[PDB]
Image (cartoon, rainbow, N blue to C red; front, side):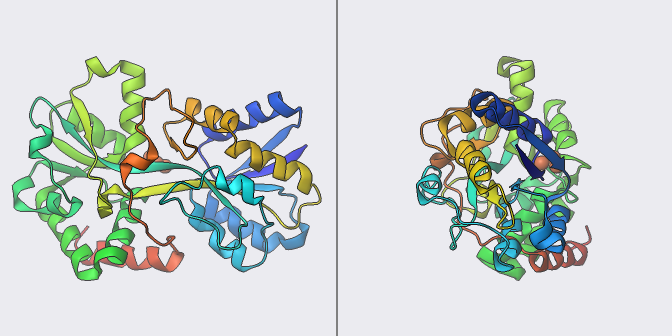
Length: 308
Ligand SMILES: [Fe+3]
Ligand SMILES: [Fe+3]
Ligand SMILES: [Fe+3]
């Protein structure tokens, strides 16, 4: 049996854990928390950690652990299972990207069509969208978007975008609130994440929704995908079962368990989500370096500088 430090949504972690125990007979104990806190605990605990695997919603959090020599190598064959073009790879082969969530524009299709949408996420923060674009400045994925903009286009462009949203956008407290605002006709469009829309669509049925999704694609900063993944702890004295779990998460069956439980994009090419997601490859996500704590501190300063 193994212990998994879990930073991923509980529905996902519980679903893949269950499917692992059913397929192998090996029991999984999840110890759940914030990935940043969990990684900190794994560094503090060092070679005394009871964690066998670290399952996360953000592969960027592996960087420090890899740098500290705390992660074990994974099989190159396992890594290749999810190694589609654009998917982050561990240079030391000591973690694996498993799935993704995407930035998206949700819009009221009875007020706008795709003809009204922008080819760049930058263009939603302009006077054409005054009073007509929702955004969630407090959300984690919004912060990831800002980091991506700074990296891809520099600070002036990112800051200008944030100023644009301050002047032209409508602020919402949460992604779910922004989605309901579009559904209820308060705002014709909003910047959110994909899984919110697909959850609403799976629950209520798409024929009963006013809102649809527009994907900017072509490696625009607005096509940003955030990657979930797993790693085995070097300190684990149960390498065989830890590696079996990670191998399982990258297998067809493990990916199937994940996508049934949550509307993330599988990174296997041969699995299809029952949420009716398009293939990962079609998203055309940009290639962006992992978010560091420094990246985040700096994006927070841009948000403040912009009046948000
Ligand atoms: Fe969240
Ligand atoms: Fe989220
Ligand atoms: Fe959320």
